[PDB]
Image (cartoon, rainbow, N blue to C red):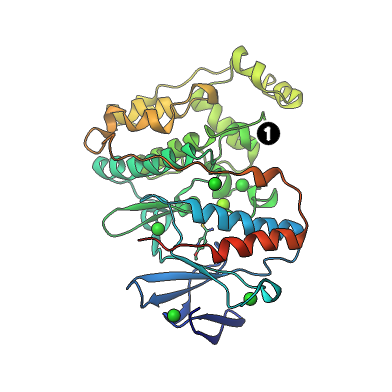
Amino acid sequence: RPTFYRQELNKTIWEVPERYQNLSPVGSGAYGSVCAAFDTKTGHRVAVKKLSRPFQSIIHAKRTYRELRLLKHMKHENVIGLLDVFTPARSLEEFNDVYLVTHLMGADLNNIVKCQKLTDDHVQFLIYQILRGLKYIHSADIIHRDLKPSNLAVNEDCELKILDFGLARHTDDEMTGYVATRWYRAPEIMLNWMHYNQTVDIWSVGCIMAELLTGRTLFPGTDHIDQLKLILRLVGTPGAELLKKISSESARNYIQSLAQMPKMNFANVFIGANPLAVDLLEKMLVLDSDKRITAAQALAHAYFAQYHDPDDEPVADPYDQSFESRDLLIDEWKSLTYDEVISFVPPP
Ligand SMILES: COc1ccc(C(N)=S)cn1
Ligand SMILES: [Cl-]
Ligand SMILES: [Cl-]
Ligand SMILES: [Cl-]
Ligand SMILES: [Cl-]
Ligand SMILES: [Cl-]
Ligand SMILES: [Cl-]
Ligand SMILES: [Mg+2]
């Protein structure tokens, strides 16, 4: 057990191993209560997150366990990973606080590229890395559900990592109005058309790629209905085959009140773009999720010819999430979390 020291940060007392020095608050709080630090064991600048009231309710205790399980599993160059996890507690009986350590991420795609169009070679490399990480995530049967520019960390060498695992589900209010937390969502999850699956993430990648190419949000709706109208103008109204699959009778009835529209010509929407980029966007932005291209298929598309290497696009170890359908008491979720803290093995 390392020696811990204490100091006052973010309105509370933090207690951390000596290896972590020069702690200072960072960020806007989107991922939790976080400080930057220097890790003397590894030489990295790191982010240290102190969980707020991790075991105050059944919902919060299970969410803490979920975040730790997801972060311990992710081991890929284009996905956030766990450098360390610790508690000052010496036993389960005194366990109360959890701290997580990751690489410090300076900039995201949003704060870097807002209102700006990038060159085609840059778009190729950035979207390639998103898809490489997504192939890994989906191979573990994990659905991200919230891919958007603020969840993509990028460094000076245009290297990219996917963020946002195991945090609270987004609320109805967070999704209301003229807000970026809805602009990248697939229509079937935005409107609860049907039981969704991992194909929702490919819709989000299409929205991101379009925005890197034009410098503009693809579907900046002022509310759910305005956004649906923008989507259907581009990709066309649903045909009878997809209407069948909308298991919400009320949603199905609203869609049929709208006048029918054909799919638009994407070469006239994305004027001047690489024809291979136009072709890939047409295969991502398909209304029927059954027919969208997958991450593994998209890596082999000719748009990525200068980066694609099928021997360097790895998949994940199996991920057991049977706990997600399990009902337990607060102290049982807390005991499971403690076991996962003390069993952590740091990366090589
Ligand atoms: C220590 O910094 C952290 C910890 C966890 C997470 C996520 N759950 S994505 C993000 N930042
Ligand atoms: Cl230490
Ligand atoms: Cl990482
Ligand atoms: Cl503790
Ligand atoms: Cl964003
Ligand atoms: Cl969500
Ligand atoms: Cl597992
Ligand atoms: Mg999110």
Does residue 131 lie above or below 178 as drawn?
above
Residue 312 left/right relative to 22: left
Q: Nearer the viewer, residue 324 or 21?
A: 324
Residue 292 left/right relative to 96: left
Read off the residue under disc 1. Answer: 192
Ligand 6 within 8 Å of the CB at mark 1: no
Q: Nearer the viewer, residue 154 or 96?
A: 96
Q: Nearer the viewer, residue 62 or 147?
A: 62
Dividing the picture into quadrants, the one containing residue 63 is bottom right
The structure residue drawn at horizontal position 45% and vertical position 83%, both measured from the top left corner, is 18
Residue 121 left/right relative to 21: left
The structure residue drawn at horizontal position 39% and vertical position 39%, both measured from the top left corner, is 131
Q: How many residues crowd mark 1 within 10 Å: few (<14), some (14–19), many (20+)?
A: few
Q: Secondary structure at mark 1?
A: loop
x, y percent for residue 42:
34, 71
x, y percent for residue 124:
29, 40
x, y percent for residue 259:
62, 18
Look at the image and tell me whether residue 252 can be seen.
yes
Q: Nearer the viewer, residue 253 or 27?
A: 27
Name the outermost residue toward the left: 306
Does residue 70 lie above or below 342 as drawn?
above
Dividing the picture into quadrants, the one containing residue 206 is top left
Residue 26 left/right relative to 154: right
Name the outermost residue toward the top: 240
The structure residue drawn at horizontal position 34% and vertical position 44%, both measured from the top left corner, is 129
Look at the image and tell me whether residue 274 can be seen.
no
Does residue 2 lie above or below 142 as drawn?
below
